[PDB]
Image (cartoon, rainbow over all chains, first blue to last red; front, side, top):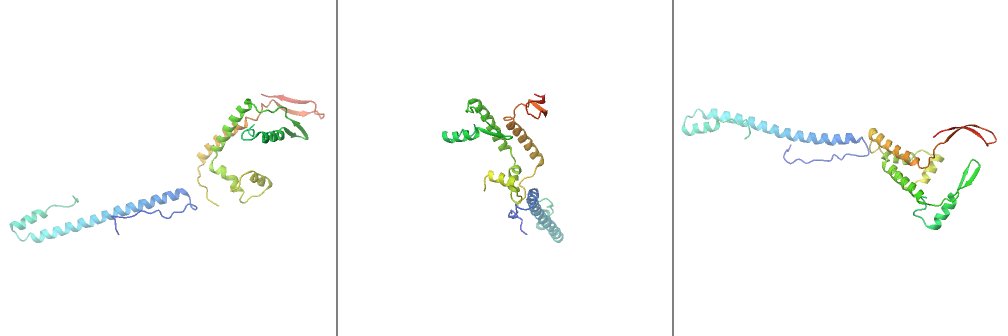
Length: 87
Length: 142
């Protein structure tokens, strides 16, 4: 739900029960799950934003193409750039 | 000799007068002139070094074995052994047969070294003896 400022945990893991190797691998798998989830969520938001902005730009340039004028053509030449890479 | 250290003169005298005696097969004997000397001090130094080494090399499981067994076993041997020791379930803290076997082999060597202090050279192995106990047939070794 919120990528930017997630917090870690200690799982309230016990030491009396269970084998210690499973304790270590459980801590590790929690850490891996957290990092994978946060990175994947950031990537998903980036993908959705890029798709939406590309579609909006395409629709806008198609609409404005009909009004052939200097300022409008300048706007078109601005908008014609691709944005597949974030920079 | 070990007791002579860390003890006062009269405590040493009482302990010496006790240790001077021995009982063996319905017979008894007394040790002549067991005075503490630098020859025995060499033995004390090497024995205490070996004893501290066997103390350090001992693993967690070896140390905890006796205390764990006292929880639910009971016998005269066990009660005597526990009475000799000081007085103050759970999964074992660490399990590692390879490291454990290496440690216990090193402790085995150290125990051998500590034991050799008191073992004499085994000169004779004996066979059947005349019933009067005077003479016997033996094999010479060492």
